[PDB]
Image (tube, rainbow, N blue to C red):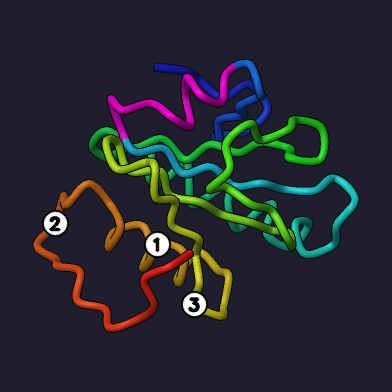
Amino acid sequence: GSSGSSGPVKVVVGKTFDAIVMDPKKDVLIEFYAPWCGHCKQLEPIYTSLGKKYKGQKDLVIAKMDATANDITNDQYKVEGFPTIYFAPSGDKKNPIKFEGGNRDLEHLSKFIDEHATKRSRTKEELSGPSSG
């Protein structure tokens, strides 16, 4: 349990990344934002609600980190363009899930979490997409 001082979205660092973002106790959604990017600005608010709202979920904590400052020791997590969201499922983290839909909003983002979520609601994963990556 961690309260939000200046926002609902939990902030993680390199020293608390492999501990939080890589917490096998619960699925943590890490979103690499850039303090020098515009897209992140329009998403700033979009993500805020996405967290404060998902705060009432099961073993789920929508956090974020500044890949620009913190170096992602991992290798599976790559930040080519911001914003960049990654869902780390408690257990199968080794395989990160980048939000790939087209429209980054509070309506689409939620549709990506509920699916890749900890199987909370009645929903399956039937996608005939690529494997590698």
Q: Residue at x 39, y 42 (%)?
A: 94
Q: CA distance from mark 2 to mark 1?
A: 13 Å
Looking at the image, is mark 3 or mark 1 earlier in the sequence?
3
Looking at the image, is mark 2 or mark 1 earlier in the sequence?
1
> Which residue does the numbered mark 1 point to in the structure image?
110
Residue 109, x across and y down, in percent = 46, 64
Asked if the stretch drawn in magenta spans residue 129, the answer is no
Label 3 element class: loop
> Which residue does the numbered mark 3 point to in the structure image?
101
Q: Amino acid at mark 1?
A: Ser
Label 2 element class: loop
Q: Amino acid at mark 3?
A: Gly
Q: Which-is-in-front pick, marks 3 and 2?
A: 3
Residue 8, x across and y down, in percent = 55, 34
Q: Amino acid at mark 2?
A: Ser
Looking at the image, is mark 3 or mark 2 earlier in the sequence?
3
Q: Check the image and report above or below for 43 versus 13.
A: below
> Which residue does the numbered mark 2 point to in the structure image?
121
Left or right of residue 108: residue 60: left
Q: Residues within 10 Å of mark 2 (few under 14, many from 20)?
A: few
Q: CA distance from mark 3 to mark 1?
A: 11 Å
- Tell me where residue 116 sits by quadrant: bottom left
In this view, the residue farthest toward the front is 132
Residue 84, x across and y down, in percent = 63, 56
| Label 3 with label 2: CB-CB less than 8 Å | no
